Image (tube, rainbow, N blue to C red; front, side, top):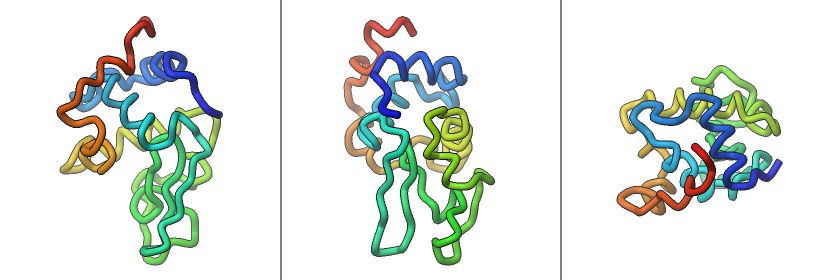
Length: 130
């Protein structure tokens, strides 16, 4: 599923993402936007390390989910990577919450540092009623 901007903003809010780990909803929107264009079935194979990024938040198979084909990988979210390709994003959100409990927080996603950190992200939630 490819979410519309405001539809996703309210979806993430209902899932408890607003201010989760000190991260505003606008930051999560900016992350999803730049990671997948709000598309839950987005995937990106990384030929260099044989891992794959899954879903709306492009969560990586080396550490967060199990796809059975990433060498020496772990599964910290204790989910099948398939769970991150569902139209319903509850599992992806629970995993994204787990990701930010690590030392880096939202900085774990390099794209957030590239297109969201120290940027004006208010635009992602304006008019969404969140």
